[PDB]
Structures are given as C-alpha cells and as structure tokens.
Image (cartoon, rainbow, N blue to C red; front, side, top):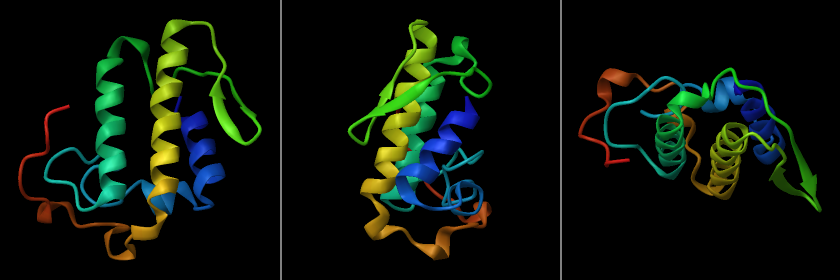
Length: 122
C-alpha cells in the first residue's frame, strides 16, 4: 500500500516523501497528464503505469511485507497481488534513488497547468 511505498522512498533516497515526491513535476502523486519533466518525473510516470495494470489489486490500500537481503528490497508476500504492487513500489524507489543526481528543486511543487504534451503509452 501507500504506507510501504512511503517507507521505501525515505529509505532509498533519504528525502521526506511528501515534500519531495508527492508534488514533483507532472506525474508524481496525483498528477497524470503531460510530458514528464525529467528522469525523476519519469519514475513517477512508470510507477503509475505499474499501478494501472494492477487495478484489481487495490495498490493504494493493500498492505504487504518487504525486507532486505544485504541492503536490497525483496518483496516478501505470497498473494500474487501483494507481490506485484510491491514490485511496482520497489522499482520506483530504486528509480528515484538512481536519479537523485538530476533531482530538480524547481519541480518540487510544480504548477500543473504548465504540464504540456502527451505522455508516452504505458
């Protein structure tokens, strides 16, 4: 669920997830239209696609377990849905971390009417 995703983000990037990732660019949080602003915004866009595919899994509220094996996130649930949503979250957190080098503070709480273009296809 959003609780696990939230933990994951903070563990992987050391950033406050609400301030740093919930209003970023065009696709983080609730945003969903426009061409993504940069790599970070793109992590948001693929994470949304990942959740779209798993609509029958209640990605936002569905709780799951995860742990680490030498620092790596391992999704640890048996329920196919819990495994899958976790995979989405995991890939996103790693994506955020792998792209901290281009994180742009100017996009933190981006004015969404500025979002132009069509995003890629999921």
